[PDB]
Structure formats: structure tokens, C-alpha cells
Image: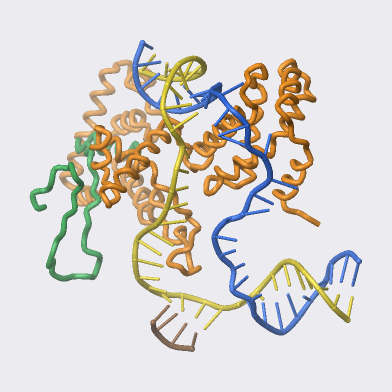
Chain colours: A green, B orange, C blue, D yellow, E brown
Amino acid sequence: TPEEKLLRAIFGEKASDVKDSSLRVPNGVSGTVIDVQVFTRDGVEKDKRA
Amino acid sequence: RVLDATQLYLGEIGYSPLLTAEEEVYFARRALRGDVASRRRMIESNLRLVVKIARRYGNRGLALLDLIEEGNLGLIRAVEKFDPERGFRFSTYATWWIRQTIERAIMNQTRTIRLPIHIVKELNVYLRTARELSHKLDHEPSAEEIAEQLDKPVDDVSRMLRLNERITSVDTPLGGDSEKALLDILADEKENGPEDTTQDDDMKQSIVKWLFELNAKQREVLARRFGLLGYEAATLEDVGREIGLTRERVRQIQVEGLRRLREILQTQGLNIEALFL
DNA sequence: CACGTATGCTATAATGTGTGCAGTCTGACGCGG
DNA sequence: CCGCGTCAGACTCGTAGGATTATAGCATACGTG
RNA sequence: GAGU
């Protein structure tokens, strides 16, 4: 919208290529992470945590 | 009485007499000449063959009647391109055309999202290869195992297997219980939120108020150039041409107006900074 | 020209379907013989 | 009359995702950067 | 599976 054109011209802050789909804790559940499991395909370079 | 489409059609085909070789040849000479009657009689006499073949190719592609019609279309191509002079029987030739046409039809129509023939046939070779692999490995094959067999890219194999992902109906009720379907859960992601709609009102209206704080000249330059209070995002030349010739002066007043807004923001920006989430 | 999508042709003879399920509920209210 | 058909059959809550198959092989034809 |  023209408003965000003007505002992003004012602040510069041109919006990046990447968004945000991070998995977060569902609201009002709260506890301790006791285990994590990672699954990667056969060919993709693995995560450091994996 | 007897109201099945299928039964009616099969009865009608039954009442046409089967041809011998010499008869087919005589008829067909005149059919290529354009006898009309000859073509009709050869078609109708050989409909029963179509049904025998469509019986085989059916199974899971399409409705039997659907297969029969496509098969008939193949048979017509065969009657148009038959060679009576060549000693080969008609039924032998027709079988090729009928099978061909049915298969091509089921490669297109069967898939909701129409898949081009090339993609479909590629995918099929991936499948048949998977079958051989699975027989001998005891295990159904991975994408990369199939790819290693073909000596090809895993990305290729993966993309094809993704396309094979078959559809789920939005109306299918969930959980073995005729309670509620997928539609009942599925959001409109594009449609925000009375929240979001009201926030745009608030945003747009706060910008009006902010624009009026500035000079009459700056505000008008900003409004016309942004296309905010104007209609069209008037270019430098357009805004200058309507006000002050100096195209350069539009840039100057515009950039000046942005910097006065920055001042308002450093002072009263305590509201503006919260627009960042 | 190439890349993506399409249209096409193949010749031993073969020529009327079936297939996968449905399981039978119940008290009422109309509709052709 | 008999018989065959069509129409109805409480309200909110929950759980969980998910299934199947297969369409040859090759040469020409049409549209876009 | 939860009250009706």
C-alpha cells in the first residue's frame, strides 16, 4: 500500500527475502524439552544439531 | 423397463452382424473411396471388439462407458487409416488404435490436475523401475535408490513423485465419522482478521494526520507522488508540471518532507516505533 | 534452434458387461396399476 | 387396496490423520525467448 | 470418548 511505500522510504527498512514459520510453544502449555529427534533426507546437508 | 445405459448400449451393438475377411476387404475398398454406408457397417460390426478391449483397460481408470466411447474414437481412426490391400486382418490393426486411444485418454482425463503426456510417461517408467527394485530388494525403493538405478538426478525423481501425490476431497469427512470435513477446519489464510483490517484503517488514518502536520507544499508533493491522497502515482515530471516546473524541486520538497516526518517520529515516534512487530 | 506440450501411428488374430460391494431399519405418506 | 418409493430420525463438546493404480515408445507438430 |  502507498502508505507502506512512503513509510519504507522514510525508514529505509526494505523488507527481507525470508519470512517466519518457526514452530513455537502452543499457548498456555509450558514444560521442559526432554528429547529432540531430527530427520533429514538422503542427500541434504545435515544440521549441526543433527 | 430396462434403464441401464450400459445394458441398452450393449444390446444395440449386439444386433449388428460380424464380418468375414473377404467381406471386410470389399466393404473397406468402398469405405476408403467414401461409401459412407460401408464405413458405418464396418464400425458398427466391429463395436463388440471395442467393448472386449475396454473391458480389459477399465478396472480403475474410468467408467466402463467412458472407456467404451474413447475406444470407439480409436476404432474410427482405424477405419479411416485401414489398408484393405495389405493381408493383415482388420481386428489386429484396430486393436492397436483402440488401446492407444483409451490409454491416451486415461493419461489426460484421469488426473484432476491435467498432466502432460511426457511427464506422465516419465513418471510411469519411474514406477515400473520401482517395482523391479522392490521385488529384488524385498523393500519398496527410496527416491535415491530409484535414481541410482536410472543413473539420474534425485531431484528429478523427487519432483515426479511429488506430482504423483493424489488429491484429497475437501468434502471428505474426517475420522471414520460423518461429523465434519476438511472444509470445516480449513481457514482462509489470505483473509485476515477484523484485527488486521482495523489496523490498516488505523495506519492509513494516522498517516493522514501526520501528512497534515507538514507544510502545505510538502504534504501535497508527498500525496501526489505517492498516489496517497491523489489518484495516480504521479511521476516527478507530472507533479512538477502541475505545480512548479522544476522537476528537481519536487525531489527536493519530497525528501524534505520525509525528513520533517523523521523529526516528528523522534519526538512522538513513541507511537510509530510500535508499528514494528 | 530449443524446450514444453501435443498430436500420432503401430498390421498374426483377437468381435455383448459382470466383480465388488449391499446389507436387509422404521413408522408414514403418496402414486400407478 | 398393494406395493414400491421418499422422506424424516436432539444439542454442544472431543481424538486423529489418511489410502490406490497406471497408462508403450518414437517421430512430428505448435508456441516462446 | 464428554454432559445431557
Spot occupied by residue E2 in the image (x, y as percentages of width and height): 39, 84
- Residue B100 is left or right of residue A49, and the answer is right
Whether B231 is drawn above or below B5: the answer is above
Q: Residue furthest left?
A: A48
Q: Is residue B77 visible?
A: no
Spot occupied by residue B272 in the image (x, y as percentages of width and height): 23, 48
Whether B252 is drawn above or below B151: the answer is above
Give the image quarter of residue A29: bottom left
In the picture, the quarter occupied by the N terminus of chain B is bottom right
Spot occupied by residue C19 in the image (x, y as percentages of width and height): 57, 56
Whether B207 is drawn above or below D27: the answer is below
Spot occupied by residue B124 in the image (x, y as percentages of width and height): 40, 38
Give the image quarter of residue B259: top left
Total number of numbered labels? 0
Q: Which residue corresponds to the image point at 74% horizontal and 15% vertical from the top-left?
A: B33
Q: Which residue corresponds to the image point at 76% horizontal and 18% vertical from the top-left?
A: B30
Relative depth, front residue between A1 and B21 = B21
Give the image quarter of residue C16: top right
Q: Is residue A35 visible?
A: yes
Relative depth, front residue between A21 and D25 = D25
- Residue B270 is left or right of residue B213, and the answer is left
Relative depth, front residue between D31 and C3 = C3
- Residue B242 is left or right of residue B62, and the answer is left
Q: Which residue corresponds to the image point at 16% horizontal and 59% vertical from the top-left?
A: A37
